[PDB]
Image 1 (cartoon, rainbow over the protein chains, first blue to last red):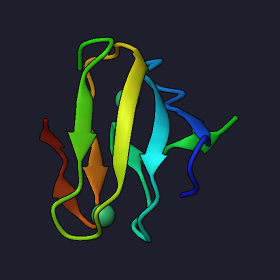
Image 2 (image 1 turned 120 degrees about the vertical axis):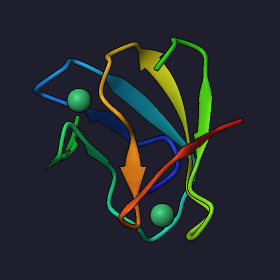
Image 3 (image 1 turned 90 degrees about the horizontal axis):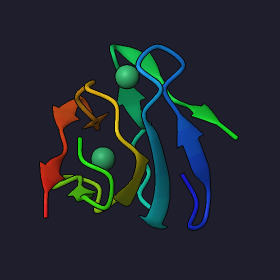
Length: 36
Length: 36
Ligand SMILES: [Ga+3]
Ligand SMILES: [Ga+3]
């Protein structure tokens, strides 16, 4: 994901912001996090 | 994870900051991210 992007786990409500991009897919509670 | 915490993927270099705590485990590149 890209710098500045915001991602949410719809299952546990966790929310993260990307500070440094990397090519992996962010996952939480076993599912792909959802970009906001 | 705790709000304000920073997590890193050791394999792809992606870095995220937690804006809202949830108890799920952050995963990237199929591996648990590491709290910085
Ligand atoms: Ga990674
Ligand atoms: Ga979760």
